Amino acid sequence: GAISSVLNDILSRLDPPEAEVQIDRLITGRLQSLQTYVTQQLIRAAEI
Amino acid sequence: GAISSVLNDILSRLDPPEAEVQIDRLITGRLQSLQTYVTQQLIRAAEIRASANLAATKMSECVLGQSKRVDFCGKGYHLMSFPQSAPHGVVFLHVTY
Amino acid sequence: QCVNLTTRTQLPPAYTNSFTRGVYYPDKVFRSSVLHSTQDLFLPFFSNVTWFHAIHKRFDNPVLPFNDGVYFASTEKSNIIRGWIFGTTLDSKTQSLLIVNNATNVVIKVCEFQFCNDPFLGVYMESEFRVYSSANNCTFEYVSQPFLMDLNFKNLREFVFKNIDGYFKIYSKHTPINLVRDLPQGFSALEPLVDLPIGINITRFQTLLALHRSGWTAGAAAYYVGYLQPRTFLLKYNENGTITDAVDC
Amino acid sequence: ALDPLSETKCTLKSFTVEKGIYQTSNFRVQPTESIVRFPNITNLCPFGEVFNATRFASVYAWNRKRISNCVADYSVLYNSASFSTFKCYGVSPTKLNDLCFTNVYADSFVIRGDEVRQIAPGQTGKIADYNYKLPDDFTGCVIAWNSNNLDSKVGGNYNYLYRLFRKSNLKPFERDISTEIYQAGSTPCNGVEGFNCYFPLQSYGFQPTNGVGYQPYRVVVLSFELLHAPATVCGPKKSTNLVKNKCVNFNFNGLTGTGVLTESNKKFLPFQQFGRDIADTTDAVRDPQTLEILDITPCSFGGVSVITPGTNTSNQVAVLYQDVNCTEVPSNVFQTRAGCLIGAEHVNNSYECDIPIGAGICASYQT
Amino acid sequence: QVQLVESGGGSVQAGGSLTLSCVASGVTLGRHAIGWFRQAPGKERERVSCIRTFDGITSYVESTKGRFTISSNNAMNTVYLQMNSLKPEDTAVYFCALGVTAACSDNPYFWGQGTQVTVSS
Amino acid sequence: QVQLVESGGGSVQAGGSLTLSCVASGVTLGRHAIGWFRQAPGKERERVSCIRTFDGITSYVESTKGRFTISSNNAMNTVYLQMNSLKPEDTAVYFCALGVTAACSDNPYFWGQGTQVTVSS
Ligand SMILES: *[C@@H]1O[C@H](CO)[C@@H](O[C@@H]2O[C@H](CO)[C@@H](O)[C@H](O)[C@H]2NC(C)=O)[C@H](O)[C@H]1NC(C)=O
Ligand SMILES: *[C@@H]1O[C@H](CO)[C@@H](O)[C@H](O)[C@H]1NC(C)=O
Ligand SMILES: *[C@@H]1O[C@H](CO)[C@@H](O)[C@H](O)[C@H]1NC(C)=O
Ligand SMILES: *[C@@H]1O[C@H](CO)[C@@H](O)[C@H](O)[C@H]1NC(C)=O
Ligand SMILES: *[C@@H]1O[C@H](CO)[C@@H](O)[C@H](O)[C@H]1NC(C)=O
Ligand SMILES: *[C@@H]1O[C@H](CO)[C@@H](O)[C@H](O)[C@H]1NC(C)=O
Ligand SMILES: *[C@@H]1O[C@H](CO)[C@@H](O)[C@H](O)[C@H]1NC(C)=O
Ligand SMILES: *[C@@H]1O[C@H](CO)[C@@H](O)[C@H](O)[C@H]1NC(C)=O
Ligand SMILES: *[C@@H]1O[C@H](CO)[C@@H](O)[C@H](O)[C@H]1NC(C)=O
Ligand SMILES: *[C@@H]1O[C@H](CO)[C@@H](O)[C@H](O)[C@H]1NC(C)=O
Ligand SMILES: *[C@@H]1O[C@H](CO)[C@@H](O)[C@H](O)[C@H]1NC(C)=O
């Protein structure tokens, strides 16, 4: 949902008050992706 | 992302239309934290259930009988086993030859 | 009577080790038997602390920089170190802060002072108050109990000054010392003393001393200055509320 | 909501309930009353001085008054119809009376109408950019009113100034009164005036008959400082008598919480005001009125389980209040290690476990 | 760069009234002294009036006192010159004059186009 | 509290026109009857005009009918008194008068400072 997937292309193009919302969107998405990875790895580790 | 981690300090300082957004942020964060806790506890419960099944099998085959299975009941040729209770667990004294 | 005094026989700056000294209670929250992690302005462990001497005719009272924070530790027996001066310019062009200790009194005045090049106080007893020619167009003022009191160097006095968003915060501690040479290899927590809502651009620091009576003598007074850094500390609150130990992360 | 068996049926979404124990709700002890412990400071805050002082300052040199150690009444301000703008950010205009602030900063000046909305966080414009700046996270109330009744003397009032030219954007809550000549570009000023050497300082010259946008406006910006510092700017709420050993709602210098207040053996250091656990939850508080340390124990709570045989067998049910003493619960009442059990008869005889209740205790339908 | 756009003036009876407006662009009124000069036929440059936009003080000459009123509204970037009690000696082209100094005494460096004011006896 | 700030008036020829403005603060026009009173030399208090801001109805006296027009714009909190056809008998100080009642008949309790209107024969 951010304007760009590249974090460095947001900071370079936006002021901190406006860059904050896009960085929050990226943080939420990447945190959810990492949590999914870690949960699937815990289940796969139980199998192994 | 809310103005304050304290929920009661939001309601006391904001009108419902404005307090709603901060309370939504807190709800999302705390719900995600609780979901993480419950998922890790389900996986840890699976691990503890596997350990408890192994302990029950060792009680059946090792205390209530003599096991021919190698190293199932410790170093050497299994003679007998004695169970002892431990905080949230079991301790087998394997007497072997 | 503003006077110039110069007989010092200057020497290249001396330095000393701060053996796990200069920690203060970061907040007003009581804690018992807990290891609490705080990100705050602390004096880093085992850091260089500059050693200024007042010993007979040697007097060291240069106008030091006031960075993010200051840790001022004076080991003394004759009660020489009496006061501190804060400001940007100290020439009455900019607002300045003054803290002087009288017998059973303190004076903390925020005025525009026409400070001397060498401000001090004089004792013959308590003879001179030769700090500022003019104390014009003053502002916020404070009076309270004296900061330092009596109850080799018998006493070491630690102070921490932090000039933060709106408050000039002073933390203090008084410790009996048998050692006379330099800082102890001990641990002491500096309990908060004052939080003055002053709000000054403080970058410019000076110390006030008392001279015993050119025709002067100082007497034994050894004071250390150590600047603060933004550090993370792990503070060990014992079961009775005291920081008994700390770890510089 | 009729009986515990109905709570079990609605929890299961089933008209028939099998034998067993089911958690249906959560018992919670409710506060008997709200107690308030604010500091007894009768001294009124000088809002009178700041709101209708004789002369307000220019926007370029905004006057800041520090408000502390006084009872503050914002209700009198909100009730007064004189003010045209009362925009509160991060606080509720109605809730301002209940709050306790560690500090207050009143910034009083005179501006024009077209820049009244310039004074609000994240705004831009001449007065916003080079005269007065508000940080993005600013918490407080901007109060503006039209005062051309006593603002603009006839023939133009040039008393109040503004800085239309400056080297850089003003920092938040920063004042720049410097009148150094600004070099706009190619020609160096060399500290003297001339062409493109625009002076920062400018004059209003309000006329008594200008447009409403062009008319003068008196503005007071109240900034609320809410650090971990002690709360000194409190409301006029009456402090109530302190109540111990009872689940109450308490307010200690702006710390609000529900709990049982007990006499604390904790001996706070004299500067200390609160206490915290390993989890950083409020454990102890200090009474403002008397220097008393009070432990705060959370009001008794816990699950409610319904021990039932099958609806095939009976409609009789027992109720287990988990980890609750049989005094907090509002005819057999039996105290177990699993909680308070109501409607089950304690029997000395030991049988095979039928319905597992708790720490060696089981229930069954018999006789 | 700075423009001084003028308006008003024209022909008017002796003893009548007129209003001259001067609006500045690329600069803001508030410190720079802004005023009015005129050229009568067979006459050199002469001051008519000035107003210090830094303080609102107004300066005139003997020939323009009372009859002419200068007024600066710095907020609309405007200066007004009101002729009252005109005389045929006032037939002149009026220039809007601006400085880079706060003083009206300093000679203006910053000129507008000019508007003709004709007074009929 | 309520202020009644007045403006306009001054000196004017007999048969000329003037406009008085009265702006209210701390109160809003819309119900309270607002009007104009005057003091002639060697004369007591007398009503000049009034307007009911609740209905916009206007009341005058014999001496002010037709020559004077009162008009309330409650939206800008303003009342205007326009003198036309002035006479030297109208030389008076005019007070802006306000009530806490909807009726113009009720005596005003709420007074403005006053503006001098001088009429020259
Ligand atoms: C506090 O005072 C110092 C000067 O003692 C200010 O530092 C100056 O900052 C400006 C730009 O803001 C620089 O151009 C100067 O070179 C600085 N001076 C020095 C001596 O370094 C500082 O800005 C002041 N603080 C505030 C908040 O204004
Ligand atoms: C002597 O004192 C005066 C006080 O104004 C000072 O200006 C001067 O620099 C001092 N002289 C020296 C050598 O420090
Ligand atoms: C720092 O301390 C060391 C001793 O460890 C000393 O040799 C050195 O001179 C000191 N330098 C400064 C700048 O303090
Ligand atoms: C001494 O105490 C008094 C208070 O009575 C105070 O006014 C004064 O500043 C103190 N110091 C000196 C040097 O007198
Ligand atoms: C003292 O400060 C005030 C600020 O209100 C200033 O006007 C005055 O000039 C200052 N004193 C001197 C001697 O400059
Ligand atoms: C606990 O408090 C007492 C004072 O009552 C003190 O003597 C003791 O030193 C404290 N405990 C520790 C570990 O310091
Ligand atoms: C004006 O000052 C008076 C004096 O105390 C005060 O009662 C009143 O509330 C003030 N008015 C406003 C609008 O604050
Ligand atoms: C409040 O009253 C108590 C006694 O009634 C007193 O001890 C206390 O000092 C008062 N509070 C303040 C802030 O003075
Ligand atoms: C339970 O109740 C139902 C009534 O619908 C009855 O038909 C059934 O036989 C009962 N079962 C037992 C085990 O009592
Ligand atoms: C219940 O409370 C009573 C006194 O109120 C106490 O004596 C008893 O020990 C408590 N029992 C439990 C289980 O909390
Ligand atoms: C069990 O028997 C004992 C006597 O040994 C008696 O005190 C107790 O009340 C009995 N319990 C019940 C539930 O009747």
Image (cartoon, coloured by chain):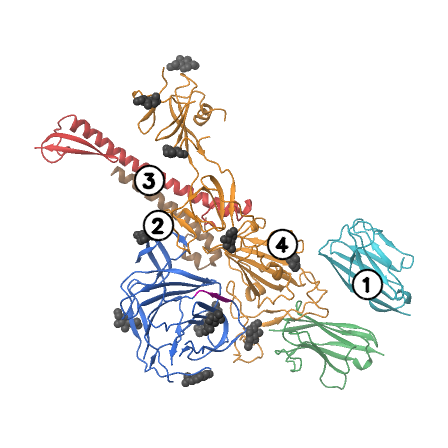
Chain colours: A brown, B red, C blue, D orange, E green, F cyan
Name, please, the residue furthest toward the left: B97
Q: In the image, is the residue at mark 4 within 8 Å of ligand 7 by its beta carbon?
A: yes
Identify the subunit bearing mark 1.
Answer: F
Distance Cα–Cα, label 1 vs label 2: 79 Å
Which quarter of the rendered picture does the C terminus of chain C lie within? bottom left
- On the same chain, marks 3 and 4? The answer is no
Looking at the image, residue C222 sits to the left or right of residue F90; the answer is left
Q: How many marks?
A: 4
Distance Cα–Cα, label 3 vs label 4: 53 Å
Residue for badge 1: F19
Q: Name the residue: 49% across, 38% down.
A: D31
Is the residue B21 above or below the residue B88 in the image?
below
Q: Secondary structure at mark 3?
A: helix
Foreground mark, 3 or 2?
2
Residue for badge 2: C32
Distance Cα–Cα, label 4 vs label 1: 36 Å
Residue for badge 4: D77
Magenta segment main secondary structure: strand
Mark 4 and mark 2 residues within 8 Å of each other at the beta carbon = no
| Mark 1 Cα shell of 10 Å, populated few (<14), some (14-19), many (≥20) | some
- On the same chain, marks 1 and 3? The answer is no
Numbered label attached to residue B40: 3
